[PDB]
Structure formats: structure tokens, C-alpha cells
Image: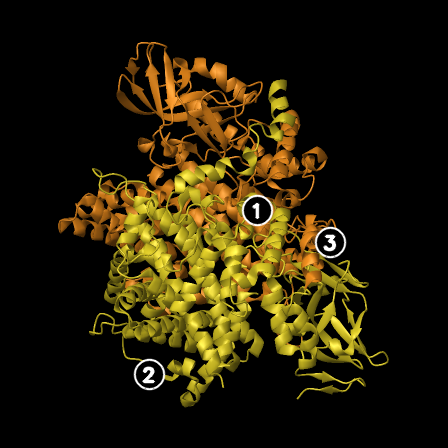
Chain colours: A yellow, B orange
């Protein structure tokens, strides 16, 4: 074999040529990406097993199908999965199931997408043991289909402004659920419109006329035998969407709908019969990597334009302009995967610092993932506009809460941390925010000090994130000191405050990437990721250059160094670029892209894909027989 | 009644309140946008007339329809259009037909989209008068449906690398068209797959074994009676796309397909029976898509209330948030700037009778900034992801309209930088003359009493010049150290593109300032002057790195610019809804539930959902056939 384990005899020699330059073993890089040699190998075994089970394959290319056909197909495969699941995976292993669903069900949704993501997690977290024995077991056995119903037509963000009520009826020991207005409809819960017969529903709890705030309730929605809506239930699909259309997102209204007292999920809150109240990230990286596999493979097989005018047309991968719009996002995909690994690691270490950072992570990773997937679509040229590239759907699913409240939630925490610093309490800062109390050197030491690592870049990101954090907080503080109301001072500062939250979040991502590289023992893997890391810190630093230049922390000369390093590591990454994406080991059945075919035979299969698409069932479209040709004949 | 002419009784009072603060007349602003009182009024008259002709309305919401249903519906409206067109518009007026097509056919395409855009102009440019009498009249009368087929599966840009051949058979006085390999297939011409029966085809012409380069041919594709592909023609649809799916983009291959000698379009080149060879806008379109999306998002922000600022007051319109204004109002400014930039380009178009390089940069820059601005979708929150916003379709269509255009400007700017370095600065064309000027030591923004927008222009000129000369000197320096020319260029190409983008953005700023200086109507001039001030501060902050790098701008001056940006956001707010209303898009054109003119979003979003196709029955076939059985069995 070769270091690149994806090469096969007969592949497109232009794509194979890009694979032969690998300096590392892609099986070993796969183990790095997925957290161990066994986790990576199990993916390959699962994929190989599915190749023997054609009943689990797409019956035709998904872009050919109407929405109605996609949902039927998704339900078809889902029932086969529940039946054969054990022959392929350990069904207790999240990760094996995540991979299995990606191969079989894809990214556009399925009727039980929310059942596992939110319904069962809510039952674990909020239902009592006695309640779990009754509902969680049925959910795990797939006897019922559930979702989580929180957001409302008129309110997405703040649980405190929801309108759905659950009023405790002491006489009958029941909760009466009610949707008082149109804007109070539950609206957007996935798989709520048509598929689910149960939901965990969030509603404001009233007892004796006092509002106890949002609580969660197990709610039957449809009859278990006929699947029709139960009396007092208004339920349905909210209509087609920009992507993710196999999920039947729904609306839900209650007309004084009664459920037992014990349908209140009571692990942590109790309401007695008398009414007494007692209160004692990886997905984004995979999507980005889907898109970059497609665009970078296609860039290896697509020849267009000349560099040297006496030499043949070059692969578009040859152009600095193409490398610049692809390779920095390969870096981000690895960077996101490694940051996700650390947040899980940090969450375990917990027995606020982390709920704040996570809010920023979701916002920044989703935005930066969307930016990169779009660059990948554009890197594909005219062909990228086809559903044969599949990137437009990859983009739409990846981009689909609201990001401004996630960033301003981190902003509140950074402002509280800036207040500690100003008042002499820097020693009280948490570890993820301690850099806010540290002292800066006069300038950045990039290209001024021998290092051979990254720490001068990390210290430079720490400086600009601290500077923007303190500047924005002092803007907020200053306006209040001049008499502005608190909340207006916050609003008048909010754009500057979000900039700080993003720089802090980006700083974390760089540090987790650097941390991972240092821990790696395999020298060929560590050098490959170190090249990626050096591209990342130079691209990201050039991206936020204004903050570095504003106070003279960086000079024009140092910024010119950063640009030269950027262009240098583009060239350094190139021989490894296809192999870095092959290491994620996505089969064609998972990737679902003609342009990103594993073997690089794009044109021949693009022609088949076109010839077999629905408008070519007949040579004369009905639009031509009914209209158009009558129109021409008449003239 | 009111300065804002879009207000009607019964509208959502939350939206009406935003229109009542208008400081200018939206009809007069409309005239500014579309180039005159008559042109704007005709738009409204065409709209009112179309309101009385239901045969020209969408039979149901377009997002409800499968692809096949969209094409049928568009074909229906198309036949009705050919009949009644003259009672609505002047068919000779490009503008009136453009507005008419947007109202009736929309943005997702139609079966004859390229018939007028490419087919007829190609005949105008290339077919002889004898040929025009036989083909151009038939096309104008719509007896045939045509397109223009140039790009190939393996080649989009360079005409010189096409593979399709047209071989002159002297014995038969015929050209033989041939597609030698899969990559030579014509691929992407709109309406080529199913609708057209003719196309003007680009091919390399071979006579007695010499290649004379690319030429154009009239080519029958389908029998005019049966419509079936003629012998030797492989033709069909290339498949579904991310958007624009009413257009049937096609592939086309030739298997030794013979066409007469006189099917070669011979206005300027002739090939005799002997074989003897005898040799001699989209900017407005992007601004409209950008305005579509901004109309929807800013309307939605006036009716969407969410969260509190002052905690003793009700939930505020999200339009209240600095964050929401910041992601909307700079893109209102860009839409006007793009429209004024297009208007100037045509003025320069019609002044030669330079330009071709600048146009290449504009197409690239405007298209990218428009996609950025449309992705308005995020400002709509969760609801913006539904097709009831319609913004995802506005995005996908706009974005299908870049590196090859920018490097074409790059070549022009490096050539201009070479003039500066070699002592020929006085020979620079006027659009590039600033490259040979001298800079003041620093920016004079906030440093001169008044000064105003010209101090911003002088700053944009400095950063565009600095980056142009720097990127050219990187290119020149690499050659002076021995690099081959084409490798030195590639190693410089990202820096060169940065230069082309700054130059193009400088042009847009200047055409905007030009328009504002020219306006006499004081309320219209002051409104657009506020937008222009928003524009230049937002755009300057966006490229601040270049301004700070040589110390041309100071940190203190950059804090001045930030204060101006936040000041003009708040200053623009009372006019924001009216500035977008001034584009005067009807609901029938706009096609957005969230951006309804009346602002009654929630009631109409609920109806829109309840009437969508998955709600025809309470229990989906996926639940009867599968879902149920799987659950019962468990």
C-alpha cells in the first residue's frame, strides 16, 4: 500500500497524484480525528458491512426526490435500521450510531431526528426515576415517537416570555395546557408536525394564579392506534424549508388540554396533589469536511486555465487563489474537531466558565463553518451550483437557535470578568479567562524571537482579545458613569461587546488546536497537523489584523511576515491537502456528491447523473406539449 | 396623505409607525432609484394593471410546487404573456419588460429565459441580414425557442480551449459538428435541455485541416413538429440545481451532425463554397435581489418584538437593537450604491461611443457583497429559514451570477502600476489616475473643519493605491529575482485580488458621492447623504487594516469612525423602512410572507403553513406504511 489508504487501482490519475504525496498514514490520522484507532476502524467496518446490505441504501439520488418521496424513503430505511441495527453496530455506542445514521439516513433529516437528540435527553434530565420507567423505556424501545417542544411562533429566545400556560387544577389534580394566542403556538420543534405522537412541552406553570416559570411536561399529542390528533390538539407541519426538509417541523396549540399532575417532569421539582410546590460542534466540523472533501477532490481533477503558457492546463488546485479559499478551512475543520474534544473534556472536569464559552463556540463555529462551506461551493465553479456537488444542501443543514443572544451571553461573562480585573481581583478569574488579568509585553514577538512553535501567536491573540474585552466593557461602564441606564448602555455597546466574545472564542479554538498538536507522539502526524496549525494561526491573525495594529502591538513588517507565512504554508499544505481530507474517511454512500466521488471520475458520472435525472424521463416535457409548442405553432 | 406612499389603512401599526417617520417622499426616491419620474411611475402602473389580470398570477405559492409543477406553471404564464403583453408594457422597453417578468415570472426562471438574453442578441451581433430575415424574425415572433451554447463540460471560460469541432465538408458544402469526448459536451446553457429547438453554438472551425478558432453556428436541435431530438443530437437536462430550477440548463453533443454552409453566422466572417476564409444590467439585478432581502428583513424587524431593553417597558422591536441595525442598514446603503454604480457604468458605456476592466471587478465585488448582505436571512431569526421568508431562493439565484473577473482587473492595475514606476504616470486613464497621485501624510478625517466625504474618498484612494502598488511590486520583485512571469503572478494573485477589490469598492463609494452631490430635492438629498455617511464609515472600518498599516490613519481617527457609524445607524433608523419601500416591490413580485407589505405576518404565516402540502392529510403515508407498524411491533 501507500501512506494514503484511500487510493484504489483505476482511480483518476489526477486525484491519485495528489494522494501519492501524502507524508502520513491516513488510517493513523483517522484515529486522531475520531479519538482512537478502534473508533476509526469501527467506522470502516460499519461502512463495509453496509455495502452488503442494499436495503439500507438510497433507492435513488436524494436530489432527484420530492419532499414527499424523501420522507417515505427515510421512514423505510429507519424501520430497517431498528430491525437490523445489531448486526452492524453496538447500539449503546453513540458514535457508532452517529456514523450509522450519517451513512444510512444522511443530513436532510429523518422522522426520529429529534427523538434521540432532545426527547430522550429531556427524559433523562427531567423525568423522575418512576417517570423514566414509564416513558423513557418506551422511547428507548421506539414504542413512541417524541420531540421537544419549546419555541413559539412569537418567541424563540427567552423562556421567560413564552405564552403557553400549564395551569394547575387542584380540584381535578390535572394540568390544563393552553395556547392563548396565535403567537403562543409551539412553532419549529423538529418532527413535531406529523411524526411524533408525544412531546416534552415547555410551558409557564401557574398554581393558584401565581406564575412559577417554565417547566416541562410529558404530553400525548396523537392517539397511539390511529395517530390522529387528540381532542384539543392543533398540530401540523409548518411548511417547506431552505434545507433539512425530511424533518417535519411543526406547530402545536392546546385548547384547555388536560394531563395528569404526574405528567409534570419531577426529578428536580415537585408539585403535590394539593398544589404545594417544592424546589429542593463535531457535527459542524464533519459538515465542513464534507464540503472540503468535495471541493478539494474536484480541484484536483478539474483542469482550467494556464499558469505557464507553454504547459497544459493546470489543475485548479494549482492556483494560490484556490488554495487560499480551501486550505484555511481544512485547518478550521480540524480546529473545530479538537475544540469539541476539549469542551467535552472540560465538562467532565466539572466536579459557568464553560456555559459562557460554549455559547460563543456554537455561534462562531456555525458562522465559520458556513463561511467555509460557501467558499468550498464557489471553489467548484459553475458545476458547484448543481445538486451533483451537494454542497448547497450541506450548507443549508449546517447553517440551520439565534446567534446574537449566544454571543451576548458570553459578553455578560466577559464584562463581569473585566469588572474583576479593574477592581484588583484578577486572582479571582477562572482559568479560561485568566488571560484577562495578565500583563502584556510592549509588542508582539512574532518574527522577533526564535520559538519554532506557536506561543507568540497565542500571546498575540490573548492580547487583542483582552484589549477588545476591556475596551468594550469600559464603553459600557463609561456610558453608565455618565448617567445612561444600564440596559441602554449595554445596547449602545453591544456590537463592540460581541466582537470581544468572538475574539475570546477564536482564541480558545487556537489554544485547543495547539494543545492537541503538542500531545501527539507520532512524528509524521504531528508534523502534518503542525503545518495545519501554522496555517491556521497566520490566516486567523491576518483576519483580525485591525485589532493587532490599532494600539501598535503589531507593525506593518510583522503583518508582512504573517502574509508570507500564510502563502508559504498554503504551498506546504498542498501535497497533504487531499490526504488530510481523506483521513475523515467518508464513503460515497455517506458523502452523496458526484463531484466529490472517491475515485475522481467526475465527468463520466456527472453525465450519468444528469441523464438519469427526472426531467429526462421523456424527450418532450408536458410544458412543451401543453404550452410552448402550441404557442409557437400559433405564431 | 403621508410622505411614505406605501402606507395603507389596516396595516400592522408596528410597521406603519416606522413608515410615518419618513423625512422624504417615497415616489421621488423611487424616481431616483429607477432613473426618472416616468420610469418609476410606469413600474407602479404595470403593477396595478397586473392586479386586474389573474391569469398572470401564481396559482399557488411557488415553494409549494415540485420542479415539474413550477415549469408547467411558468410555461402557462409564458403563453399568456405572449398574447397580452402589449396591453401592459411597451415590449421594446427593456425596463418595462424586466419589471413585468419579475412580477409575473419571478426570479426562479422560465422556459424562455435565454431566448431574449442571449439567443436574439447573438443573432443581432453575428447573423447576416439574409440570415436575420430567416431566423431573427422567427425568434422575435417566438415561432422558435433558442439559447446560446458556448461553455462545455470541461471548459467554461476560455473560448480558445473549447473542444467541439465544426468541420467544413467542401464536397457537400456542409459543416460537420462533432463532440469528440465527454468533456466537449455543451453543458450549462439555460433552456437548452428541454425547451429550445434551436441554438447558436460556439465551435472551433476546421477547413482543410487548419483550425481558424471559435466561430458561431445556427443549429437546429429538435424537429419543429415533434420536438424530438434530430438525428445525431444528444440533448437533455443536466439535473436539479441549488436554485433557479425553472430554467432547464442542458447538455448537448454532436455525432457528426451536418449543417449547411449558410448555418455559419456570417455578418463579419465568410466561408465560401470554396472553403475560402474571408476575415474582417446585472448590477441593477444584484441591487434588486439585495433590496428584496432587505425589504423582507427590515419589515420583519419592525413587527417582530423580542426581549426587553429597559426592563419596565414591553418587549422591543428587534429593529431597536444596535446589533440588528448593524447587520441591515449598511446593506441598505450598499444596494443604493450598487444601483448608482450601475447607472454610472452605463453613462460611461455611452461615453466612449478604462471600462472593461472596471466592469469585471464590479460584477465580482457586487455579487459577493450582495450574497453577504442577503445572508438579511439571519436577521429574520428562526423564521428566516422557512420558505415563507423566500430569502434562501433570493440568495441562491443572486449568487449564481469570480476569480477570473478579478484577475482581469488585476492585469489592468499592474499595467497601470508599471506606468507609475517607469515614469509614465501622466499616461494613466482617468479611472486610474489616482494611482499616480501623491498622498498627504495622513488621513484628514476628523482633522479638518468640514472636509466631509471628500476626506473619506481621499482615504479610500490612498489605501487602494497603496495596496495596488504593493501587490504589483511583489509581482515585479519576484521576476527581478528570476521567477518566470506566470509563476510570479500566481505567487502574487491573492494580494493582487485584494488590490482589485479595493479599487472597485473605491469606485462604488465615488459614484455614490457623485449621485448625492447632483441631487436638488433637499429631502431626498439629505436622506441619501445620511446613507452615504453610513456607507463610507462602515466601508472604511471594514478595510481599516490597510488604513492603519502605514500609520495613515491613527487609532484616534478610527474611534472617530466608529462613533460616526453608530451615530448614522440611529440616524438612518427613522427612514430605514421608507428607503426600502422606495424600491416599490409589490407582494406579488416580492413573494415573501415575512416581508408582506402590510406587516400582518403571524396570521398569514399560520395560513401559509396550514395550506402547505404535508398538511393535506393528518396521517402521512410514512406513518401508515412504516411509522405505525414499527411502533406497534416494539
Q: Badge 1: few (under 14), some or many (20 or more) residues near its Cα, within 10 Å?
A: many
The reply to whether label 3 and label 1 mark residues of one chain is yes
A468 sits left or right of A4 in the view:
right
Q: Residue B265 location, x and y as percent?
A: 40, 19
Residue B103: % across, % down: 62, 39
Q: Chain of mark 3?
A: B
Q: Which residue is mark 3?
A: B619
- Which of the chains bears the disc numbered 1? B
Relative to residue A169, is residue A29 depicted above or below?
above
Q: Are marks 3 and 2 in contact (CB under 8 Å)?
A: no
Task: Kindly identify which residue carries mark 2.
Answer: A439
**What percent of the width, then of the height, locates residue B9?**
74, 52
Mark 3 falls on what kind of element?
Answer: loop
Say which label, 3 or 1, has the lower sequence index.
Answer: 1
State how far apart marks 2 and 1 are (Cα).
54 Å
The answer to whether B39 appears left or right of A582 in the picture is right
Label 3 to label 1: alpha-carbon separation: 51 Å
Residue A214 is at least partly visible in this image: no
The residue marked by circle 2 belongs to what chain?
A
Classed neighbour count for the residue bearing mark 2: other residues with Cα under 10 Å, few (<14), some (14–19), many (≥20): few
- For label 1, the residue is B29
Q: Is A593 displayed left or right of A555 in the figure? A: right
Where does the C terminus of chain B fall, quadrant-wise? bottom right
Q: Nearer the viewer, residue A208 or B322?
A: A208
Please state which of residues A355 and A77 is positioned toward the viewer in this rendering: A77
Q: What is the count of numbered marks?
A: 3
- In the displayed orientation, state which residue is furthest to the right: A171
Amino acid at each position: 500500500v501507500h501512506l494514503n489508504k484511500t487510493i484504489q487501482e483505476g482511480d483518476n490519475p489526477d486525484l491519485t497524484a495528489e494522494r501519492l504525496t501524502a507524508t502520513f498514514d491516513t488510517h493513523a490520522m483517522a484515529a486522531q480525528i475520531y479519538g482512537g484507532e478502534m473508533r476509526a476502524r469501527r467506522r470502516r467496518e460499519i461502512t463495509a458491512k453496509l455495502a452488503e446490505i442494499p436495503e439500507l441504501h438510497d433507492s435513488m439520488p436524494l436530489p432527484y426526490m420530492t419532499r414527499e418521496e424523501k420522507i417515505m424513503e427515510s421512514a423505510r430505511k429507519l424501520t430497517v435500521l431498528t430491525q437490523r441495527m445489531s448486526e452492524i453496530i453496538d447500539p449503546t455506542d453513540a458514535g457508532e450510531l452517529y456514523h450509522l445514521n450519517n451513512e444510512v439516513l444522511g443530513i436532510e433529516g429523518n422522522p426520529m431526528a429529534l427523538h434521540g437528540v432532545m426527547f430522550i435527553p429531556a427524559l433523562n434530565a427531567q423525568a423522575s426515576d418512576e417517570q423514566q420507567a414509564k416513558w423513557l423505556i418506551r422511547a428507548l424501545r421506539r414504542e413512541i415517537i417524541g420531540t421537544y417542544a419549546q419555541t413559539e411562533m412569537g418567541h424563540g429566545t427567552n423562556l421567560q416570555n413564552l405564552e403557553t400556560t400549564a395551569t394547575y387544577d387542584i380540584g381535578t389534580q390535572e394540568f390544563v395546557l393552553h395556547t392563548p394566542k396565535i403567537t403562543a403556538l409551539k412553532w419549529w420543534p423538529g418532527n413535531l408536525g406529523k411524526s411524533s405522537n408525544y412531546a416534552v412541552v415547555v410551558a409557564h406553570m401557574y398554581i393558584k394564579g401565581k406564575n412559577f416559570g417554565p417547566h416541562t411536561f410529558m404530553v400525548p399529542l396523537r392517539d397511539e392506534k390511529t395517530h390522529k390528533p387528540l381532542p384539543g390538539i392543533t398540530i401540523g407541519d409548518i411548511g417547506p424549508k431552505m434545507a433539512y426538509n425530511i424533518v417535519d417541523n411543526g406547530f402545536l396549540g392546546f385548547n384547555n388540554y388536560r394531563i395528569p399532575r404526574t405528567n409534570l417532569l419531577m426529578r428536580h421539582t415537585k408539585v403535590e396533589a394539593d398544589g404545594t410546590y417544592i424546589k429542593p460542534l463535531t457535527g459542524q466540523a464533519i459538515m465542513l469536511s464534507y464540503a472540503l472533501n468535495i471541493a478539494t477532490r474536484y480541484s484536483a481533477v478539474r483542469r482550467q486555465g494556464q499558469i505557464d503558457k507553454n504547459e497544459p492546463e493546470v489543475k485548479v488546485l494549482e492556483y494560490q487563489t484556490q488554495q487560499h479559499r480551501l486550505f484555511p478551512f481544512i485547518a478550521r475543520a480540524y480546529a473545530f474537531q479538537f475544540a469539541g474534544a476539549e469542551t467535552v473534556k472540560l465538562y467532565e472536569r466539572v466536579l459557568a466558565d464553560l456555559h459562557a464559552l460554549t455559547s460563543g463556540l456554537k455561534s462562531v463555529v456555525t458562522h465559520q463553518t458556513g463561511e467555509g462551506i460557501e467558499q468550498a461551493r464557489m471553489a467548484c465553479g459553475g458545476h458547484g451550483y448543481s445538486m451533483a456537488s451537494y454542497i448547497s444542501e450541506i450548507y443549508g443543514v449546517a447553517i440551520g437557535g439565534e446567534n446574537m443572544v449566544m454571543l451576548l451571553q458570553l459578553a455578560r461573562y466577559l464584562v463581569k470578568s473585566a469588572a474583576l480585573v479593574k477592581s484588583g481581583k484578577a486572582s479571582q478569574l477562572g482559568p479560561l479567562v485568566a488571560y484577562l488579568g495578565a500583563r502584556s509585553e510592549p509588542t508582539s514577538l512574532i518574527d522577533r524571537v526564535p520559538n519554532g512553535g506557536i506561543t507568540e501567536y497565542i500571546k498575540t491573540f490573548q492580547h487583542i482579545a483582552k484589549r477588545q474585552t476591556l475596551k468594550a466593557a469600559n464603553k459600557f461602564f463609561g456610558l453608565m458613569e455618565n448617567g445612561e441606564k444600564r440596559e441602554i448602555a449595554w445596547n449602545k455597546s453591544s456590537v463592540e461587546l460581541n466582537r470581544a466574545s468572538r475574539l475570546h472564542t477564536r482564541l480558545f479554538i487556537v489554544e485547543a488546536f495547539a494543545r492537541r498538536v503538542n500531545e501527539i507522539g507520532d512524528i509524521t502526524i504531528k508534523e502534518a497537523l503542525s503545518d495545519l496549525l501554522h496555517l491556521h494561526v497566520n490566516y486567523e491573525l491576518l483576519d483580525v489584523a485591525t485589532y493587532a495594529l490599532e494600539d501598535g502591538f503589531m507593525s506593518s513588517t510583522q503583518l508582512d511576515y504573517v502574509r508570507d507565512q500564510l502563502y508559504f504554508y498554503l504551498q506546504k499544505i498542498r501535497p497533504n491537502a487531499v490526504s488530510l481530507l481523506d483521513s475523515w474517511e467518508f464513503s460515497d454512500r455517506e458523502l452523496r456528491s458526484v463531484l466529490g466521488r472517491r475515485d475522481g471520475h467526475v465527468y463520466e458520472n456527472l453525465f450519468k447523473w444528469a441523464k438519469e435525472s427526472p426531467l429526462n424521463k421523456t424527450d418532450v416535457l408536458p410544458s412543451v406539449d401543453t404550452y410552448l409548442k402550441p404557442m409557437m405553432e400559433k405564431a
